[PDB]
Image (tube, rainbow, N blue to C red):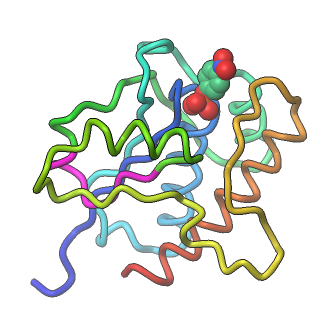
Amino acid sequence: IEKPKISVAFIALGNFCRSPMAEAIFKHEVEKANLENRFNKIDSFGTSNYHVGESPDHRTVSICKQHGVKINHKGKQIKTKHFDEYDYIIGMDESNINNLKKIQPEGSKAKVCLFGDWNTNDGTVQTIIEDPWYGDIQDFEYNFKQITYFSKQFLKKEL
Ligand SMILES: O=[N+]([O-])c1ccc(OP(=O)(O)O)cc1
């Protein structure tokens, strides 16, 4: 087939604040655009195992609920083997990218990229989805705006 079903994995450090939000929003945008048929797996993970088994940060959940975006997730860690199970392994910031590239096996199919690679750079949003941990609910809302923006760009540019 010329239009293969795509598998996407969103990565952050804890799979607690940003990546579960990225997965939730991306699935939401796929559904709104009736593009389910173009995707196999859409998941989120963390480079660390610090929040394995836990539901997302209450602030990420509150932001998703405020926008009417469903979210249901338990923390999980990205592994070297996953690089052959996903077409895109998308990090939030450069520190995520650094770690992913160091565990990326040679020849694996996944393309490691920054979600912000899909930014238009037209000034609407910043490219790096910054860790909101030490910030507050506004930083989480901004991550939501960034992720929604890149999700729509990704759907328009990669399919
Ligand atoms: O404690 N922390 O610094 C911390 C913990 C979990 C986080 O979640 P992430 O956005 O999925 O990496 C982000 C930051």
Residue 68 position in % (x across, y down):
72, 48
Which residue: 76% across, 58% down? 145
Quadrant placement of the N terminus: bottom left
**Residue 4 % position (x, y):** 18, 75
x 43%, y 59%: residue:
113
In this rendering, position of residue 37 left or right of residue 135? left
Left or right, 86 with respect to 98, comes to left
**Residue at 16% of width from left, 44% of height from top?**
105
Residue range of the region highlighted in magenta in the rendering:
83-90
At 78% across and 66% down in the image, what residue appears? 125
| 42 within the magenta span | no
Which quarter shows the C terminus? bottom left
Counting the numbered discs, the total is 0
From this view, report whether residue 4 is shown above or below residue 20: below
Instruction: Locate residue 40, reporting x and y percent.
Output: 25, 58
For residue 132, what is the image quadrant? top right
Res 38 → quadrant: bottom left
- Asked if residue 158 is positioned above or below residue 60 in the image, the reply reads below
Which residue extends farthest bottom? Answer: 2
Percent of width and height locating residue 51: 50, 14
